[PDB]
Image (spheres, helix red, strand yellow):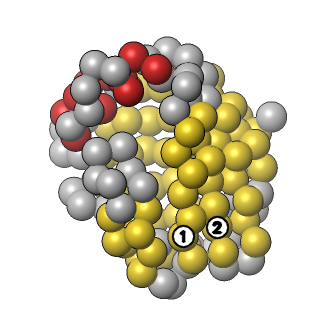
C-alpha cells in the first residue's frame, strides 16, 4: 500500500545519474545530498507523488492502466502507462529509464536504471 510520506536515508548514484540523463549544475546542486520526502497519495487506481529534494518541488499524477504524462527531471511531460503488480510493486519505463518503485514494508526502493548507472533510493516511511 503506497499511501504515505517516505523520507530519503541513502541514495546510490544521484550526481552520476542526473548529469547522464541531462540536467545542469543548478537542479543537481539543490538535492546533491539533501534528503527529500516523497509524499505519495494512493487513492485506489489514481496515484500522485510529490518529491521535495532540497528546494525543487516536482508534483506528478498517474492512473494505473492509463497513458499519463509525467513531469520527469529532463523529460518535461513524458507519456507512459504505469503497470502495478499486486499493490506493492510499480513497473514503468519513461523514455529509456526503467523505473521500478518496489515497496518493502516501510522501505520504498526506487531502482531507476538508465543503462550501466543504477540510481537506488532507500526511503523509509516517516
Q: Nearer the viewer, residue 11 or 69?
A: 69
- Residue 88 as seen in the image, left or right of residue 75: right
- Residue 62 as seen in the image, left or right of residue 16: right
Q: CA distance from mark 1 to mark 2?
A: 5 Å
Q: Secondary structure at mark 2?
A: strand
The mark tally for this picture is 2
If you read the primary sequence from the N terminus, does the residue marked by circle 1 or circle 2 appear first? 2
- Residue placed at 24% from the left, 61% from the top? 95
Other residues around mark 2 within 10 Å, as few (<14) / some (14–19) / many (≥20):
some
Taking 7 as reference, is 39 above or below it? Answer: below
Q: Nearer the viewer, residue 27 or 90?
A: 27
In percent of width and height, residue 33 lies at 49, 15
In percent of width and height, residue 105 lies at 74, 48
The residue sitting at the bottom extreme is 65
In percent of width and height, residue 97 lies at 28, 53
Does residue 106 appear anywhere in the picture?
no
Q: Quadrant of residue 123?
A: top right
Q: Quadrant of residue 92?
A: bottom left
Q: Are marks 1 and 2 in contact (CB under 8 Å)?
A: yes
Q: Nearer the viewer, residue 47 or 90?
A: 47
Other residues around mark 1 within 10 Å, as few (<14) / some (14–19) / many (≥20):
some
Q: Secondary structure at mark 1?
A: strand
Residue linked to disc 1: 62
Name the disc covering residue 47, or none.
2
- Residue 4 as seen in the image, left or right of residue 99: right
Taking 32 as reference, is 12 above or below it? Answer: below
- Residue 111 as seen in the image, left or right of residue 15: right
Amino acid at each position: 500500500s503506497f499511501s504515505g510520506k517516505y523520507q530519503l536515508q541513502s541514495q546510490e548514484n544521484f550526481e552520476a545519474f542526473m548529469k547522464a540523463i541531462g540536467l545542469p549544475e543548478e537542479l543537481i546542486q539543490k538535492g546533491k545530498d539533501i534528503k527529500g520526502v516523497s509524499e505519495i497519495v494512493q487513492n485506489g487506481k489514481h496515484f500522485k507523488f510529490t518529491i521535495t529534494a532540497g528546494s525543487k518541488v516536482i508534483q506528478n499524477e498517474f492512473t494505473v492502466g492509463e497513458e499519463c504524462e509525467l513531469e520527469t527531471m529532463t523529460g518535461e511531460k513524458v507519456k507512459t502507462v504505469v503497470q502495478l503488480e499486486g499493490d506493492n510493486k510499480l513497473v514503468t519505463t519513461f523514455k529509456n529509464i526503467k523505473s521500478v518503485t518496489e515497496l518493502n514494508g516501510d522501505i520504498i526502493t526506487n531502482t531507476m536504471t538508465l543503462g550501466d548507472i543504477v540510481f537506488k533510493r532507500i526511503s523509509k516511511r516517516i
